[PDB]
Length: 331
Ligand SMILES: O=C(O)CNC(=O)C(=O)O
Ligand SMILES: [Mg+2]
Ligand code: NI
Ligand SMILES: [Zn+2]
Image 1: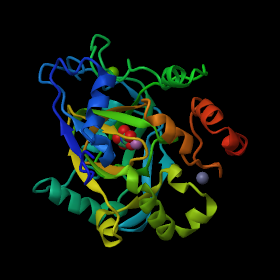
Image 2: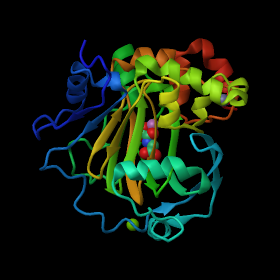
Image 3: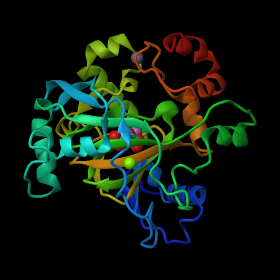
Image 4: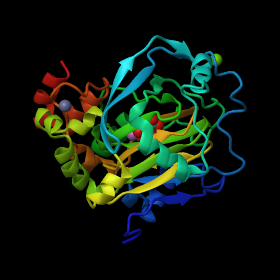
């Protein structure tokens, strides 16, 4: 079995190997990359997502989210308070202000220490889930706006034609902005490209050990667990690496820098934070190997998780028994 310790693998495709997205994902899995839950892909040196970022300040963040924490430093939840719209130019200025800017630090490890020590005492503002793309239309390789759609993959594998579309989303982050422990909707893959700015640190649990993380989460967030049998779908709970180590949960960590892709694999729980002002783009995708994960994916039916139009069909076709109850949650 390849990669039996479930380490995060890093890949350096040639420009030739960068032509066929599906084939390269299948290559990575042949080397065991999926066992980690997360892989890094460094694009060939000849490749670029677009010519410059010089003209992005007029993008609108219509609903910036202030991420308010509750709990203790290593075990907390966050809630998203909606703020007034601002442009990316305004947001970048805010990120760079004395109140919100990255503190002086020695290196990534020192910054990670400061994050876990101090995150809960601040409320950084996150521009999340903004439909759109920063890939130039002329970028032909690994253009997250030109991937084959999950609906087409389901059709190719299973023969069923369904409604729905699949488009990318932009994330504008600042110091301490945080992504809570989650898997993707319907335990899909995700791909994330860090277009610009400061790094993003990731933590990941191997898919084969995901239930260990869930069990811990039920112990650490006991009221949330009683309210919903899939409450990590709410995307609000954080557990530090120290806490994960104290409870024996297998995980890995890696820092993504500007110009790098990360791929999350089905049922790979991940969480992380941004080091300073940055802009990422991400999208879900599927492969044939995903189908069985989609069939087994947990679902939130308490009504909190409230997700896209396109997830309807996935639940309807892959999880017909659940469909009824899940849709009660979504209405
Ligand atoms: O970058 C972020 O804030 C969150 N991204 C992801 O969870 C992802 O790409 O799957
Ligand atoms: Mg602009
Ligand atoms: Ni994700
Ligand atoms: Zn729920």
